[PDB]
Amino acid sequence: LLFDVPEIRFTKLFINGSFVDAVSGRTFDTRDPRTGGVIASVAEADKEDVDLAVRAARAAFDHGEWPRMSGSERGRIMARLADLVEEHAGELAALESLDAGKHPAVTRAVDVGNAAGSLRYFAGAADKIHGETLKMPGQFQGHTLREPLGVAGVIIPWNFPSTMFAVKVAPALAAGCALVVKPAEQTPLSALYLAQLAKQAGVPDGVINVVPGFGPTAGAALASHMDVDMVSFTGSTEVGRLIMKASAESNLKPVYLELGGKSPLIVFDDADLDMAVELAVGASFFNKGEACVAASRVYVQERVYDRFEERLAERMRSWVVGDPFSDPRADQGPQVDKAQYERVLSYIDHGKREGATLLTGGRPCAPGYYIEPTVFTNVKEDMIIAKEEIFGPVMCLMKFKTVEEAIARANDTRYGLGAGVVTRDLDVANRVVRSVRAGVVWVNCYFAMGSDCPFGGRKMSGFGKDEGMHALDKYLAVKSVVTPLRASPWI
Amino acid sequence: LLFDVPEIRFTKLFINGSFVDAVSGRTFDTRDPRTGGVIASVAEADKEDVDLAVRAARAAFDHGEWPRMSGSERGRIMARLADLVEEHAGELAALESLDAGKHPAVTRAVDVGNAAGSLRYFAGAADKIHGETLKMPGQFQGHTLREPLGVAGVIIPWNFPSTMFAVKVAPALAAGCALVVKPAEQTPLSALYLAQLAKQAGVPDGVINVVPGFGPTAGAALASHMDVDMVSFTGSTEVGRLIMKASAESNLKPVYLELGGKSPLIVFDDADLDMAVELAVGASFFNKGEACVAASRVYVQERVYDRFEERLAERMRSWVVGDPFSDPRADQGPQVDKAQYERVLSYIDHGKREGATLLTGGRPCAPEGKGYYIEPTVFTNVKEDMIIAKEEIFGPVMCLMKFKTVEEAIARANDTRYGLGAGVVTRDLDVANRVVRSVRAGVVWVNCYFAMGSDCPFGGRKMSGFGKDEGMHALDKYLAVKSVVTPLRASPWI
Amino acid sequence: LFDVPEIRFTKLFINGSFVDAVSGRTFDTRDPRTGGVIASVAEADKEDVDLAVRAARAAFDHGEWPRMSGSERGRIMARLADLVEEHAGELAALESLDAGKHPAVTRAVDVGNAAGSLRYFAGAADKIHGETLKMPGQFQGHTLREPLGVAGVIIPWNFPSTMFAVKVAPALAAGCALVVKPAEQTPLSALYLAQLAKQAGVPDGVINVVPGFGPTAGAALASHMDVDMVSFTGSTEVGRLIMKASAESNLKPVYLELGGKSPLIVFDDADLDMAVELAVGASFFNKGEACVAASRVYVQERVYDRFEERLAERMRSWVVGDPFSDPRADQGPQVDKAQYERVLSYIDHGKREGATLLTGGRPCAPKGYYIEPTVFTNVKEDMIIAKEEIFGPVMCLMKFKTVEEAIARANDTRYGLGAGVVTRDLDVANRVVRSVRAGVVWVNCYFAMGSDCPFGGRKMSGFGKDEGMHALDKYLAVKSVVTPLRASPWI
Amino acid sequence: LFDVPEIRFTKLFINGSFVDAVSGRTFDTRDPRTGGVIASVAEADKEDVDLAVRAARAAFDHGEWPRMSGSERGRIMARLADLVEEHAGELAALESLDAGKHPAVTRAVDVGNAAGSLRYFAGAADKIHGETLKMPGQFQGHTLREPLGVAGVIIPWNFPSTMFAVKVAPALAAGCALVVKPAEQTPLSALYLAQLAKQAGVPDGVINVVPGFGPTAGAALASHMDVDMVSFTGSTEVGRLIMKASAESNLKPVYLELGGKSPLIVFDDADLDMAVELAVGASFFNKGEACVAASRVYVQERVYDRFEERLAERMRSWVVGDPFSDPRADQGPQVDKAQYERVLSYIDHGKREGATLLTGGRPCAPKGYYIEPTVFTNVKEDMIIAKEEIFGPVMCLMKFKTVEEAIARANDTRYGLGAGVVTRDLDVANRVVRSVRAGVVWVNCYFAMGSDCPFGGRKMSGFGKDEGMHALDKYLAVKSVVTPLRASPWI
Ligand SMILES: NC(=O)c1ccc[n+]([C@@H]2O[C@H](COP(=O)([O-])OP(=O)(O)OC[C@H]3O[C@@H](n4cnc5c(N)ncnc54)[C@H](O)[C@@H]3O)[C@@H](O)[C@H]2O)c1
Ligand code: NA
Ligand code: NA
Ligand code: NA
Ligand code: NA
């Protein structure tokens, strides 16, 4: 082939520094979306396995070395882990690509690079986490201590396996927490590989526990656990409801939700059309639309709409959908599995039926679970395709007249994850940025953030931040301490 | 009477700057725990009234002046409100005290003073709320904007009505949010009075909406509302479950929970026994134990235990339970209502039945009547597994226990589902540091209790909740953090 | 017409009292509209500075002010802001008569910013924070942000009330005691403000005002062995003497707010009518007696000719006259005879070096120290008028071709206080803002800041920030506190 | 025994190369154990400083370093930290022979703190933040935290590696170019560190090392017209000259880390054996050649007699000798002949003024600059030995009655660098900590800080912080940016 197919080494659960089978001895299969065939038979975690992993994390936090280590010591190990992710980038990229149906070179440069980058950023945060010394109403000394919380429960999706693992694990490790990670059943391989690398880096046993299994089994047990201090969840808005219920029905642990989106990209009259078209293609079709922040709604101002529409249709004619391991041309790979592939085509079918015009794509291909990049035109705001998260290579292209109209239409969603603005006008950019109810707003770009940039939703896209110093908050216990002072010359 | 009984002026719902009746025309009574008699007939808000209030708050945020005003402008209006609370402190104190069964002088100095203080602290925060300018991975400029969130839903308890109103309203107002406040049905008068004073201060119509009603009606409607951006809740751990469910079943709005507690107070052998006893009395019995952070569990080291126990029983002999409006000597007033009175009496009876020793109180009292008066109760020979040791009584009940080691004191302090507050009484700096850092509580007082100020963040750990009330930390729940990224062309530095 | 105020405060303000100088000496303050004596002010020297420093030392070491809670200090500070607002008209008329200003402009701008600075720091007082640090082992570390002690303040004549408030407000909030040396040309506002502070409840000894001459009273304060810091605002040349005075005494930290030669850059992009109106205000506000005045105006070649013609036409309706008797008055007299002659000397020098006189360039007096607003065209960068701070109503109007040229020319100064950019282009705005070595950069506006905005120079314009939470730093002592921990379950 | 290192780097380090001085002049560095020449080091003067400043100017204005991302600068700094760790033994041996230190103490303390400071700031590089401000109307305001430019560094001979790192690390992270003037007595470590920084990937011109004499090389750097700031560490008397050099040149901000006369307070409740052992280390670490050394020890009257006796018996087992040949060696020789004679002069002066000699007070040498650790009893506060910085193994042991007396006596100094408190009482500890006017206060310990802990003087011990996120401020330009907003839905 073009890229070397990796050898599957880690298929068991990772509890207390060891690779172990499920209590039941049950396995679940992970498949290659390029072929639809079984890659590996992975240990199937259930309630009993989650209990064992939570017990291992509890012992690691309450009695283990990790919270008792200096921030410098924790950051030292976290950096060695970042070094290992970088050293084994190629292997990890192919392993994630084969499991998630993506391009190994894109996975290495984007996914693995961001994973290593997130680990490095928090390794540098570990020795500089600060609390405050407060201003008191009298002869008192007050301060806050920013303590490790305890046992962190992590539930993540299948679209960015390595990045999802790092973005949750990294701020939790720097905070001094012990972890229980439940990766998505569709792509469980990267999380098990990363667990082995953390062991090699010097992360103490019990600090990182990986429990691959099904959501209503393993995931629900973790979200409902009486000895888990917090839960950081990334997935659908509908499953987010169940995570909130699981906490309410258990120990009322704080819940942090990174949910779906229906991200709008607004293109103005003054934009360079060639850059705006190229930006829109990337924004909508990166990772075959299996991106939470994907620009599923593209808004183009009436004066340049016809030109944009023509240039977009022309650009899509040179776009290649195929096997990233055998085809060099390949711009897009297959969808994660059978269930997702049926779901996108059903939405394409819904789009056709409700009266939307098909500009490009709208049908399956195969040189596997391949769908061509779809662009819907003459889209009404009330349409299913306009409102619902498709999570596939589907773009809704719309026309607008005013700045006011662009703002109101961008905000006409239950969601509020990301948004984009393409304009040269400083006053238009400022107005649009400040008026769109989204957690992240890109101006004349898309996706670009870095680990210093906090990422989180607004409205039904969730709450809580991943990345930035902001990410640490969910993993820390803020403790206020008050004592009287005797004859202090100042207060 | 020693304190003037106030004139009840505000009994209707406060929606879009006006005092209006409920859509149903229904009322609910608020009673005086000193007599058991009706003070006023308050408008009963339901689903329809909460919608009206949320629509008023939505119009005020989306199209009104409040989020469009500068932090300085919001700050001046907030300081005028703080000035009004101070100017009308006596009337508000009398009103809250008659509704809650409090001492008017204590309420003025503590409750009203903290309410005015929280409004002032956030008035000063309004013109200095900052976001960041970020460090980017290349030729990019990144920044965060700390925007007003939108419509803030507030659900609060009956124990500190004025303080609860201010502690939620003040950071929200400073953040530039519009509010919908659901006060507890037992004490709804203060929230209504405060709403009128905000109108006088210059708070625009629709920014503060007060909807008194029942929890499963008006409270559930607010927590389940599809157009409410966040919910800040203060109340029991059991109702907290329903707030989280209401969000999950609606628009998944962020929820912030300020829940119950079973706060431990640890006294070591090196303590001054007279100060430690006097501190324990205040920590346990302030506001007749109707305090979330009340030291319901007192742990005294074995060498000084017998002396502490004797000094505590002696101190309680001079404690006065009675009418704060007619008796000057009164240290403690009646419990909020009949329901709370029976609930505390049931826990005392349960305590006796499980084998705990009654050191003092444990029975009803006090003046010629009439009134929900309970003697401050101290339980001795309490086992950790006992109901009285684990459950929140929310009455004048203290569980007195003995301990040997620092390690034992820590483990026993942590033997709770809760983690709101805790106290340490010691002269030893190393013991104080170890106990402070080992007790899983949101607030730890060393050689004092309650003292915080508005710069001090307050929030639970474990089943006592999450999220901070007070401090600059309080603003977070009312703000939307927006990350903004743009490329840079030929910047000489990054 | 505006009512001429009655002068009531002419003595030194030491330990809560209005006292005469030890010598019994006075110095005259004059009205630039007539050149006549307004009042005879007590002349402070070394002995009076000693008395004021001793009063501040007693107030800090033994007095109430540092022992009060931030909340208590905040209420007193806010009462002072309320008083400045209540007496705004009287203070504006007083400052206007003394400095040759328009009483309505002084009320809206100068007095409003003074009241605003006091309010901002009143709200800062109860929320000043230190940190709880991340330690290398079983240790607990924290920083305390303590009041420093005795703050020495030396300020100029151009913005008397604003200068007083901008130094006094963060010092007051920090819990410091003060010794203020106002400029001899305008000493009246400071003495009025001192009385207002006493009425607000500021304890005796906390605010001491010692008007006098720079080499006498000013040098004594800068050289004092018991002064903990010096905040200086004035010329770059006097700044040298403040640094020497500290070096020759107790090596107290020095904070310098020096001169400027601020550039305003206008692109082809700009609305010419708004750009001309902005330039007029930026160059001629307070008769060019502004440190941040746009003394250099750069206009891109394509719109230069139109800008130049519109500017000359705009200046034809500009009124220079008595602000107390003429309603149309846009500009008052220059502060005094010395400043008046210094500006005329620079105008004459400009003519002699070959620069074209577009408008003004000669005295008016409708007798008074009135100078016509001056615009110089065909200005070479090497010219005296192009490089030196004139501090009068003089604008140097220049032409440019490229963004690169505009940046290089803006930076061709020893100074770096302020700068301005007029453009609709977001990328041009970002590039110029980030490339111009100035403390403040205004985009499509000028002067606008507010008390949350830190103000300070770069290069020879100084160092240190006035305004913002940043202004508190110079008045605080950061104390690091370290103790071991015994068996802490986390670090 | 320990291995004597090879001397490899003896030339100036300018623009990535080891070059000779323009004059071709050299100065000798000597071994304090023998008094013999170790190496002949290139002697920098005005011309060499000019060359180094020009190299730093080109590196900042046109080079890669300020244009690289914080992440990029952080990886290079972490590679440098890794190299300092890899070559720790060689560097410790190099610094030890040059400064008269124990190679094992230099490795664990000096080299460990140097590597630790580089690592802390490598982790700071990708997370330096400015603010987005609260505006007085329809305006958007923000601050940018820019690299300042050319940083001038002047450091002492006592902690060569630590001094180099503590100045270079925040400056590097900030994106500055540097010119380092190390002390003439110990120039070797700085040249070795410069070579390691080249190996790590620090671009040419970013780190320039100019060993030379103070009034020549040092004065030229402090007076340079193209240097943006100066961070100085040394004596209080030389600090005066650094302030004068900036005042007489370009008025660049100056940051001073000066001398001290640090008090250690021991109360009646202390464990005498721990308090004696702590005092021994606090006074005699690095043969009293420590700025923060506890040169004044105050013991409460009830435990004074026991403390005094235990201290004299503890000193009987203390070994002064060659650390390279004697394993028992607790103390090495004084840096040079000049320092040796200066300490002996102070000991002789102490005897002359009436102070009692408890231990030491005479030379030892098993020849080569060895002085016995000296303890003076019956010391009056007015004595020379009580007030002046000896900078040798000399301790003044005094008795006190009250907490109030301990505070007033601790504060009876022109200095305010460090202080220590030994007590079990939480209220006494808090009162002493908050009442002693010192930048650092250790409670029941000494020296312990870590790189998160800011270090700086108060009073005549200076101003400005080394270490912590606080250390970055001096190397950054804070730029305020203001623009109007059109129809923003919120402000
Ligand atoms: N924010 C700022 O940066 C800012 C603001 C306003 C004005 N300014 C600057 O102020 C200058 C105009 O004011 P000025 O003419 O009053 O300046 P100046 O330098 O002559 O004097 C300023 C102050 O210093 C005193 N002074 C003079 N000689 C002294 C000495 N030897 N020792 C100690 N103090 C001494 C004066 O009495 C006065 O109080 C201009 O250069 C202008 O740019 C700067
Ligand atoms: Na798969
Ligand atoms: Na009631
Ligand atoms: Na005058
Ligand atoms: Na040497």
Image: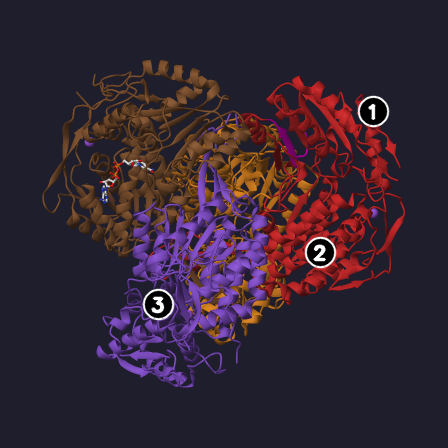
Chain colours: A red, B orange, C brown, D purple
Q: Are marks 3 and 2 in contact (CB under 8 Å)?
A: no
| Segment colored magenta | A412-423
Is A416 in the magenta?
yes
The subunit carrying tag 2 is A
- Kind of element beneath mark 1: helix
B395 to B121, vertically: above or below: below
Q: What is the C-alpha distance between the residues marked 3 and 1?
A: 82 Å
How far across and how far down the image is residue A255, in percent?
A: 66, 48
Q: Is residue C145 visible?
A: yes
Disc 3 element: loop
Pointer 1 local density, CA inside 10 Å: few below 14, some 14–19, many at least 20: some
Left or right of residue C197, residue D227 in this image: right
Q: Nearer the viewer, residue B416 or A304?
A: A304
Is disc 2's CB within 8 Å of ligand 2?
no
Check chain identity for marks 3 and 2: say if they share one.
Answer: no
Q: Is residue A434 above or below residue B104?
A: above
The residue mark sitting in front, 3 or 1, is: 3
Residue B317, visible in the rendered structure: no
**Amino acid marked by disc 3:** Ser
Q: Residue at x 48, y 19 (%)?
A: C302
Give the mark count: 3
The amino acid type, in three-letter code, at marker 2 is: Glu
Q: Residue furthest front?
A: D24
Q: Residues within 10 Å of mark 2 (few under 14, many from 20)?
A: few
| Labels 1 and 2 share a subunit | yes
Name the residue tied to disc 3. D262
Which residue is located at x 29 percent, y 82 percent? D357
Dot label at residue A87: 2
Task: Judge left or right: residue C164 versus residue A354.
Answer: left
The label shown at residue A352 is 1
Q: Quick one: SS at disc 2?
A: helix
